[PDB]
Image (spheres, rainbow, N blue to C red):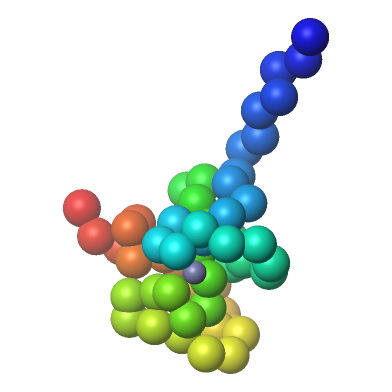
Length: 56
Ligand SMILES: [Zn+2]
Ligand SMILES: [Zn+2]
């Protein structure tokens, strides 16, 4: 067989769809650009961090 495992996900953690997803520079989670909190639009310049990390 095979491990069949990966470090980071490959699906939105809000709507769960296919396509390009953002990556966090800390944890191992992915979030769309419109499915954020707060929501995003363009490429968030500078070290970006998901709202799940900044929060407890
Ligand atoms: Zn989404
Ligand atoms: Zn994170």
